Image (cartoon, helix red, strand yellow):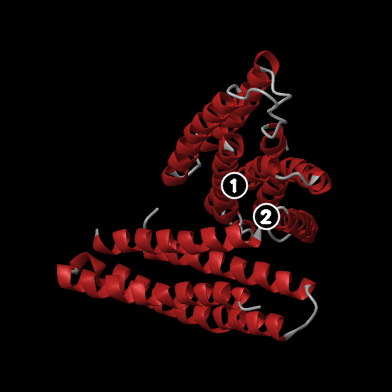
Amino acid sequence: GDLINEIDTFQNRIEIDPAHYRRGTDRPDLEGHCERIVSGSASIADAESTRENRKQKIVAECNNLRQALQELLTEYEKSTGRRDDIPLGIAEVHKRTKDLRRHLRRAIVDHISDAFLDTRTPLILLIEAAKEGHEENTRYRSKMFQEHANEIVSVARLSCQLSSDVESVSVIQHTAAQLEKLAPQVAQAAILLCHQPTSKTAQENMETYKNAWFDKVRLLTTALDNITTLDDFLAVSEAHIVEDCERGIKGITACETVDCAAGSIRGRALRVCDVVDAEMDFLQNSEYTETVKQAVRILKTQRVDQFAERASALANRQEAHGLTWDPKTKEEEMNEFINACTLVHDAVKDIRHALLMN
């Protein structure tokens, strides 16, 4: 990962003995160092998968980092005699750098949150269509599965830029290349099964590809969680659950449907359960871990089901008589959806709260 190394080293490069500072050498490379950070940050910011509000924070902090560096360099060049203002300048740069990297890390978590909220369904829907074998659905689900594959591959590679874990990055990159290789073959295996569904040879071939795929995705998901800070993941997950609710609200009052919004919320919530449970199991068993796992168990075994049930009933009411909804009904259903989402959302906040109690 280059961008993370550029940032990490920069936080040390700017700390020079004032007597050692030389304008003609220490300034151009420090300015060059800063611009490499800004350039790399821009690539992340200006991805069209990147969210707008996080994009602007990255842009703003890049400008702040430039300004902070210029002021520090101005102070370095005012040192005389034997050589209080320089350390203040260093602190200002460190603060901007710290904020910039938080924004970048969470930009990557944005992608991880979206791409890995449901890594099972696209292939399952593909296989089930092929088993029928529904030609029209298999080709549709084939296309969707492949696009899903492109996303997790792309996101995996994007993540590596912000990790200094050379060995984890190595596994992630190899696994991503293998998935990229396997994906079109998995698709074709389903097409073959679709055309001859009663063939046990074609059934076994699909299952062989299915299992190889899920084994690699599981590996990749685990590796990515290992180069991701838990707090970032939970903070973004919580924020994304709110976004999903807002998307669902727009569908009720006017990818903005109750069905899909509920699908995203469920997936993200279950990912939160997986990631926090694993984090606790690595620890020694204590009152701390049991209290956190208990909060997780509430989300997973209660809140998720209760949410899915109410959201589904709302979805059924909208396809049944939604075409006749007056503003009052829309308001009632909007509130019902909000209260349902609050089931999941509050439970996520409780999990984060329990993790603080040590």
In-front residue for pair 168/126: 168
Secondary element under disc 1, as helix, strand or loop, is helix
Location of residue 275 (image quadrant): bottom right
x and y, in percent, of residue 279 in the image: 72, 69
Circle 2/circle 1 CB separation < 8 Å = yes
Circle 2 is placed at which residue position? 228
Query: Seen in the image, is 46 located left or right of residue 15?
Result: left
Name the residue at the right extreme.
Answer: 167
Dot 2: what SS? Answer: loop
Q: Residue at x 61, y 31 (%)?
A: 37
The kind of residue tagged 2 is Thr
Q: Amino acid at mark 1?
A: Ile
Pick whichever of labels 2 and 1 is earlier in the sequence: 1
Q: Percent from the top left, x then y, of residue 303?
A: 50, 80
Foreground of the two, 177 or 127: 177
Q: Which mark is residue 352?
A: none
Q: Nearer the viewer, residue 283 or 266?
A: 283
Is residue 121 something one can see in this rendering? Answer: no
- Rendered-image quadrant of the N terminus: top right
Q: Which residue is mark 1?
A: 108
Q: Nearer the viewer, residue 324 or 9?
A: 9
Residue 5's place in the image compared with 77, above or below, is: below
In the rendered image, residue 276, in percent from the top left (x then y), is placed at: 66, 70
Around disc 1, counting alpha carbons within 10 Å, would you say few (fewer than 14), some (14 to 19), or many (20 or more)?
A: many
